[PDB]
Image 1 (cartoon, helix red, strand yellow):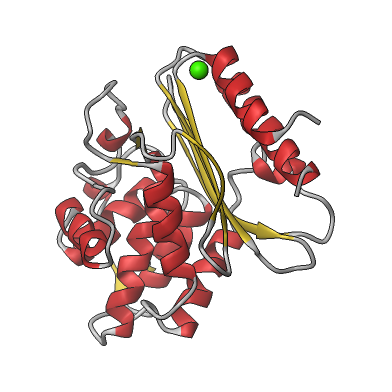
Image 2 (cartoon, rainbow, N blue to C red):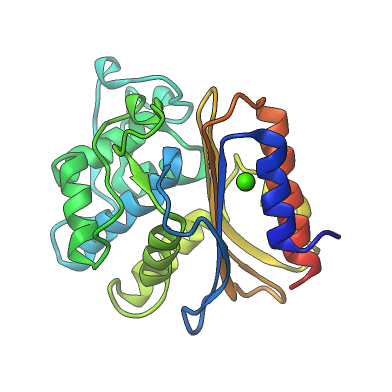
Length: 263
Ligand SMILES: [Ca+2]
């Protein structure tokens, strides 16, 4: 029931640290609302969507195939690998890995996909190459979550991320089938229930990706809208506090409720 910017400011008051927020119109790309739009925040697992965008760019370039099967070993497994840990014998396809990275936040999957393109610096280069000179990936999972206060590694800004997400989902940087694949994976997110999904009315569409660190940080990127169709991009980041996970989740959910009620 509070106005969305009011609610975002309130969340920051409650949590400490910073909260960043942007809402973009999907069709036009115009900024509808924002708070701290140009300040940096750790991406956490929200980067996984961008990683898959790079993968799909390679598929569209004829340099990768979503059906290519990747065998990996137990030595490749890192923390929070709920899907990849189950496929040591069979491996997983590149498309399966992106599904695991996005829908389940699987870390080994993300590292595997990062190897396909040559590592974090090469994801940065992909972003630079599509006009995003702000967003940067520097580390692998799980270190990219360490969220050291002002250390600009592995960070984006609300506007950079929102703008880049829109460019990946709409327009022609990716083919229609690749744009569609990316949003499908996001729609199938399984691990963001406490966040914007908790506020979502029946019949709405959401495609999202969340991020978390143990302490300090949370975030979500989303394309959502009524009537089965996304019409806006929302990006919310939080960092720099000592808030509990339950309180970070609750604040995101409340920001979501405000955004939906004032749509
Ligand atoms: Ca403040």
